[PDB]
Length: 262
Length: 5
Image 1 (tube, one colour):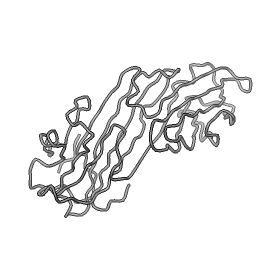
Image 2 (cartoon, helix red, strand yellow; image 1 turned 90 degrees about the vertical axis):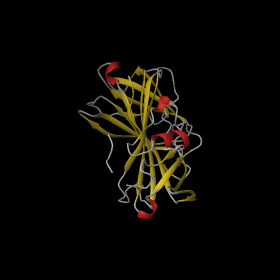
Image 3 (spheres, rainbow over the protein chains, first blue to last red; image 1 turned 180 degrees about the horizontal axis):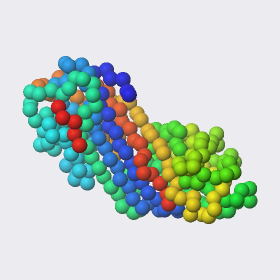
Image 4 (cartoon, chains in turn red, orange; image 1 turned 60 degrees about the vertical axis):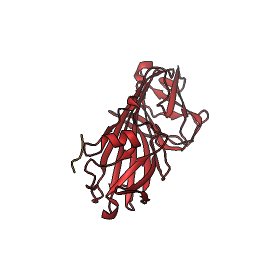
């Protein structure tokens, strides 16, 4: 739970994405919610202005505003405000979801993908199984920390990371589980950087290695932070007076959900 | 869905 100095705007996006084994993009789906937390009653009679970049009338996003929000004012002036012009938001510091969106992209379209993935498999001499290379490239601006790759086998023999061909080679097996499978953590994927995670693992046949899933999370606190799809705040403002600015912080985040290769 | 207020 982030700390709130009066107004805290959380822009949270969840990315689903799917690839073939060779890295060909099958599909993606991005979901978003803008959350508002207010804890000082003076600030609760407020209006948010969205960044000049964002197109609120772009229908591919299916922008839906909370029922109490003035839908028309959102569409004309990119203003989060209330129907009842004299009502206020709660000052109770509870997370109020006021705007949502969802966008999808088709096969071979990378516009919603923060982390592209490719896999290669050839058989191994060191175990009854396969030498795997997972190649990845972030197009994010920040670093990802503690990315987890899960391979849905529970082997008998422990997994051997290839420390030579893995980019971020303190990479380690964190667990091996009968239902959840085998999870490898790598500590960093740096901004706009291609890497690779090489290892060897015991499996009865190639198809048992799939689906491979990845798990990751980016968070950034900053007034000028932009979400992965370009959601951002321009200002916050007294509902009754649009020149009178108000103090506020923004968190933007991006976490994966169904993010996989098979 | 949406939180009432």
